[PDB]
Image (cartoon, rainbow, N blue to C red; front, side, top):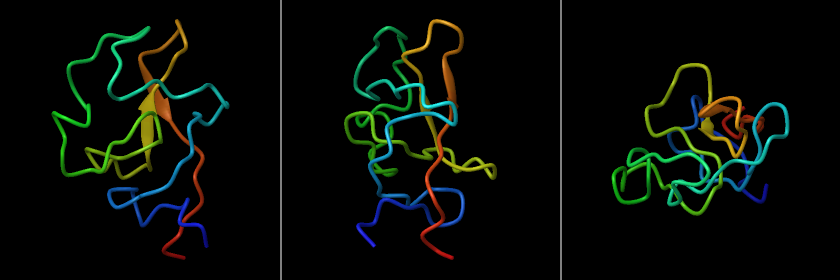
Length: 86
């Protein structure tokens, strides 16, 4: 596959999904915008492969990969990337 898929929780999810389960665009892990988060950035989590706004699981939530949303409703949510390790 093009490797836009997660392995388990998405800890080694090296994909490029950029939307929550709703399709709400994931914010840039790098951007505090419009959700300021000096956490789960590429620079605070240089082990979970956080690039741009592509979904990731820095914490390896056992529910799956997530991101921060550009949605003024919630700070973060889960993404909808298929299981690569399946």
